[PDB]
Amino acid sequence: NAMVDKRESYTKEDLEASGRGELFGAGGPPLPAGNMLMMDRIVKMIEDGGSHNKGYVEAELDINPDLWFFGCHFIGDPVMPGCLGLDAMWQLVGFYLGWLGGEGKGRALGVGEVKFTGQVLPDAKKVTYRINFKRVIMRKLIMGVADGEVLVDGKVIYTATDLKVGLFKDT
Amino acid sequence: SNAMVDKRESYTKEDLEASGRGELFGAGGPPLPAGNMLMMDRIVKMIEDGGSHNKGYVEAELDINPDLWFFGCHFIGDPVMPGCLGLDAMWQLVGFYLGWLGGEGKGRALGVGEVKFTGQVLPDAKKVTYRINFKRVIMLIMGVADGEVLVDGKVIYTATDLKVGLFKDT
Image (cartoon, rainbow over all chains, first blue to last red; front, side, top):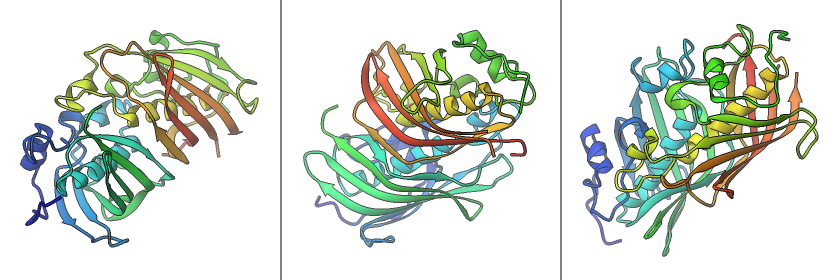
């Protein structure tokens, strides 16, 4: 919890290093790698920023027509699964806890209401994730609670209330 | 409504693969996803008047082995099935049930009310079970349901108010 002079943005290379457990300390929570990594860059991180003044992170995914999920979901009718945008938000909550200096391995613990009101199609350009923290709890289990939004090409299409993620010392 | 439905009480992996190709409910009904987004291997039970609200009960299974694609990438050093993929399995089953009843269109998950994860699927697990209890079926075709995910017989996720619609024009 003594970590200061924090970076406010991260590149794709940084996100891949995180997947290897090589961005933060070896004890920090890694992002998923490969086909489960659902963003290309983190554009903004602010401690005590965001809609509740308790933390903010903004990230982006470039929507390339060759993204793996388009081919299989659904065949000949490509659309990004909402569940993967939801996971992207969970991953960002966990990442933010690690960014503060939290040690452990991340596990999504749940979410309140999730609404999918639009779709991400291959013809889209960019998905944006906006995460607004409500609670940061530095206990034996480090826990983050946040509200999230997913935008496609600048318009909000998903909302999630009370995303919850924990960092476990031992799973 | 879609009259071209192959309506049975259980479905095999071949049936699920056929569904991904649109061969179970035909041109007018909702296909399942395929490949690495298909999150079950069979549907064990479908009961039209069954479940908590006497509106539908569906049970399905995913066989677990250490080589499933998601284990390798989520996370390196700490393989665990993403909860979101079990949620998707349940959303897909809600859409599938709508099609099974003759619903016309392509499925789209609309959201969920509340989700609690109290456990995890590790690569040394053997079976994941999905249990879906339908609460509302509107035949604007949509379904509202509660779902549970178990691993090796133990409940690890609950999801209330899973919602899916069928859209003739996505």
